Image (cartoon, rainbow, N blue to C red; front, side, top):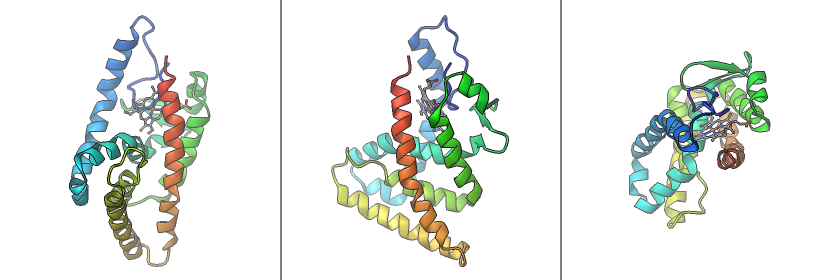
Length: 196
Ligand code: HEM
């Protein structure tokens, strides 16, 4: 089994080589990855970062961007995960196929985010913040990335205050999702790299 919803299905043909399995999986997740690249190019200040820092932000942050974008695949009420094919699998079945604490943590994350029911504009600006907030270990011009982060966070505060003048705490709640995403990213990378 391959219990990642970026796949078309969690079932693996055991008579395929590791390479064929990855190739097929890549045909499923690659369009999503390319969509994050096009999204990043549309953050105006992103293009002013060095080419190295652009690539490194995408390398570190693509997972967190997609986690936000695809939080709606996790239906906490139905306890189902929708895979990129549109097929749905119960949490129980996925656990029997080898999913565990990480899947549970993503449900918890998605439930809390899904429940905020952000508008498209709010979700899009939050996602920009997520990308530019990516792990900085690979970054050559930290101050430039921090400046862009600050600019986007200010825009997000302004948008949230417009849209939620009596619930400003939504802005703080969104910032507090950043270390949660970093945790999901760390745990997920461990699972990704352990895949045999
Ligand atoms: C291109 C991006 C991604 C790749 C290449 C990838 C790959 C993988 C691989 C190889 C595994 C281990 C599968 C197994 O052992 O059965 C995994 C686990 C998983 N991934 Fe992904 N993934 C990606 C993005 C995402 C995203 C964006 C999400 C959430 C929206 C996600 C959700 C999950 C879940 C729920 C698991 C199982 C967690 C558990 O074991 O409890 N993946 N991923």
